[PDB]
Image 1 (tube, rainbow over the protein chains, first blue to last red):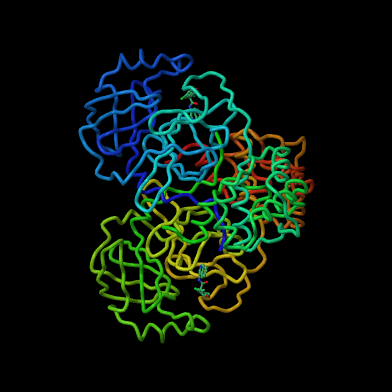
Image 2 (cartoon, protein in one colour):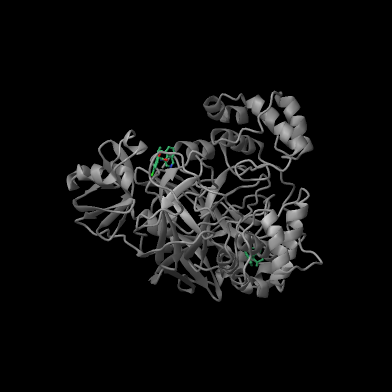
Length: 304
Length: 304
Ligand SMILES: C[C@@H]1COc2ccc(Cl)cc2[C@@H]1C(=O)Nc1cncc2ccccc12
Ligand SMILES: C[C@@H]1COc2ccc(Cl)cc2[C@@H]1C(=O)Nc1cncc2ccccc12
């Protein structure tokens, strides 16, 4: 028992982290096979970031200008190319530690682990969610760009995120591994509206099931609700509308505990309306939305 | 910016995880050099756990009875010995992936990362603290015993914890790497009093400094306090008494923000007395005590 904001073991991703330097700009790169993937803003100076013409900036760069270092060894760059907001530096050596991998585009509300890196060296790993407004509430300092987000299915690492920018609001934005931004962000130092965020309802419910599994049962009540009634409360509290697909996704957790999905929705409704009255659920004094139903089943079953 | 419950990258510890089986009991082992360290209860059956005589139980076991497997390869056991509550199985092969390491005994209030393992395979990593009553609030299922806790100083892994037991209360207990239990626990399936826990005051203050660094400043007030006055409030709320060593440990954070340690104690006092009035600090609706002043400086500076 016990429930933690657990991250995937970062070992398979630690072996891919390299440092990429171009001019006076240094950030992190991801070495898979004979390709190093890094944010394209590695070619910009601090001044360039205000309004960069990346096509023009890259035109001034050659293979020898991209210095790629893995630990203490230099990688020879035999080709560079820009795909959306990332740079792909083809190196002459395939990474001997390349794990099985995929590049995936996660959906908003999905979770992933981030291995925060500085100068190609990993500093820590943490679990977080893609917010419904396509931002992440990470912990990133200058030089952390190129740090990646991922999920792990036994031996296959599914890379979903690459860190690029911190918005003036202190929240973070990045791309999938093909350089496409999650959300409406552009890689320019300008004010960018993140948009209204909502709470991931399916995730809060999944975490309520985890609390029941792990002993916290005080929030369970003698009530039930319908999707339409629950959704009226969800709108009032800026929670994502719950659909039948969210209910179906909660199926196994509903089976485990025997608490019908709509009955748990009625528990969430009373918590939204009445608060927690100074009590905790799984050590939290708020309603946690960074655990998916998949995460909850995985953590409570033991999936390695 | 941003502040997360970040764990150390688990890669150097993933390479040490093995599966140890004895009879019908399987748990996790830690392979460093030519020694595999695992909880001594691997020799017990479910019945033995009620009142085990480990000296007698081990007398029935030989080197060939301990099956040690790393991934898909079998390790040859050339010697076994019991040190306190751990077993040391000498193997004929040194682990090719042994990192630089130390065995340390952490102090209550200190933090560490845990790589939860099942059948010698890592499932996830999470950051947690040694509670003042020498328990940990982990996330551990059956078969997770032998999972280790650690800290990492550049390339040196300092192993501080090995998981052994889940108390009826749902909290967890374990040993240092020399098999000594943290706290008064014995490795028997009997009711064991965990003892009164307190909140780690130096850690809450450190996290208040992190919130100031990262933007949350609403809890700052026009007040100051003394150690004696603050400690009277600390006792009333079951918080650890703050000493001058705790103040000195908070020195660098006090310098960074320019908020005197006693001024921050006065902010904590008003939060204890008035609550948070439905507001959050670093995304939490309670007072977080699982970040040490060292953790806060490390995360806010970028230490790799
Ligand atoms: C500094 C500029 C601002 O404008 C843009 C604009 C676009 C892009 Cl893709 C990057 C940046 C840079 C940035 O946000 N980098 C960072 C990313 N993460 C954490 C950071 C912590 C502190 C300092 C910078 C961080
Ligand atoms: C089950 C017995 C109980 O008595 C003792 C007594 C002493 C010892 Cl050192 C181990 C155990 C075992 C135990 O707690 N193991 C576990 C440790 N962690 C998580 C667990 C989740 C579920 C089931 C067991 C877990």
